[PDB]
Amino acid sequence: TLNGGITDMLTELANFEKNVSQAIHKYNAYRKAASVIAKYPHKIKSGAEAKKLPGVGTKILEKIDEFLATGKLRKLEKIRQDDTSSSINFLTRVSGIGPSAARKFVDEGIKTLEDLRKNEDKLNHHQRIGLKYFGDFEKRIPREEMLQMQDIVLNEVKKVDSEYIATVCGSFRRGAESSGDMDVLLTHPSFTSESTKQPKLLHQVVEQLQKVHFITDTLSKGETKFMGVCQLPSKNDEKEYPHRRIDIRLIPKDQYYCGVLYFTGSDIFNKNMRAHALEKGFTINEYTIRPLGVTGVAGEPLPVDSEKDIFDYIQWKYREPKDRSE
DNA sequence: CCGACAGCGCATCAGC
DNA sequence: GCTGATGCGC
DNA sequence: GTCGG
Ligand SMILES: Cc1cn([C@H]2C[C@H](O)[C@@H](COP(=O)(O)OP(=O)(O)CP(=O)(O)O)O2)c(=O)[nH]c1=O
Ligand SMILES: [Cl-]
Ligand SMILES: [Cl-]
Ligand SMILES: [Mg+2]
Ligand code: NA
Ligand code: NA
Ligand code: NA
Image 1 (cartoon, rainbow, N blue to C red):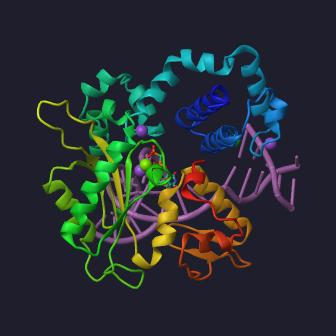
Image 2 (cartoon, rainbow, N blue to C red):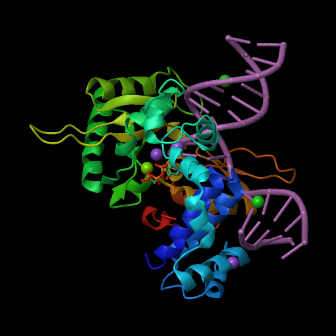
Image 3 (cartoon, rainbow, N blue to C red):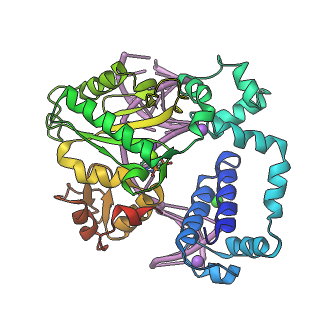
């Protein structure tokens, strides 16, 4: 938080470009700038000083100078008074409502939390649960609660079958004091890149976690990716815990290290690392690292026995999860 | 000093 | 229904 | 919006 005011401004600028301008490249440029400033040590005192960091060009620089001068950005002070974009920004905070849907609702005259309530029929399933738990999903999760959710999820998957391996990734694996949701990587020997012997492996896990009333709702469900809602159990007379977003991602066991690298993130770190693989002539996704040819087509998967192997290939020093919070 | 910008699962739609 | 495009979230 | 070429 040495340049919290600046990175906040940049993050709000990015939010606007994504939600209102629907210019996803402006969005990503601001958030690259926000993150490189966020880890930059000591107080930024000038747009030109900032300019030295990669991803900050002239326009961010003149914005930083204005912010440092006045404490404000006029550009944002008008965005915050513009009633239409302010309504669009707000609706995208419901999970499952993004730019298109947010602007669709606002055109129809549906502009506040109440308006969504008076209309749960114009909302797809994901959007209704996002609305149901709107206040809950804006709350972070203390690591202590994350640790309890970890023990539940793990002891339940082992109840289904003792060869499941579940790994809590996301901000938790990076060591964060709090997380926005809970991310679970799931491997089972039966499911590799060679074939799935029998699917439903993710369903059985979801089913069990539901039967014990940990998973309370579903946002999306498929054979390898579950997105839903879960809740810790409270004790007698105690206030209930908030409900929590939970994503579970089943990955071929032979592709674990690529999957755990993917799912540990952050999303910005994943994007730098993948852009850098491409410059090195490699492509990385959550399953494999593969060489880039001369034509550009991905070659065949390179062999991987650790996260560090992935790093070695693109000639990065190994970064521990803790230092991946970009 | 203009093209590329990371990559993919699931849900929903439109045109068959 | 299937295919491919888009929306959304990760 | 930014930058490597
Ligand atoms: C949103 C997003 C995510 N991920 C990968 C990396 C994430 O670390 C991981 C988990 O997604 P998410 O839970 O949204 O991010 P997080 O790092 O755990 C931050 P929070 O604690 O708020 O969940 O998915 C991406 O690779 N690209 C993305 O755009
Ligand atoms: Cl642009
Ligand atoms: Cl489809
Ligand atoms: Mg998370
Ligand atoms: Na720069
Ligand atoms: Na949303
Ligand atoms: Na997540």
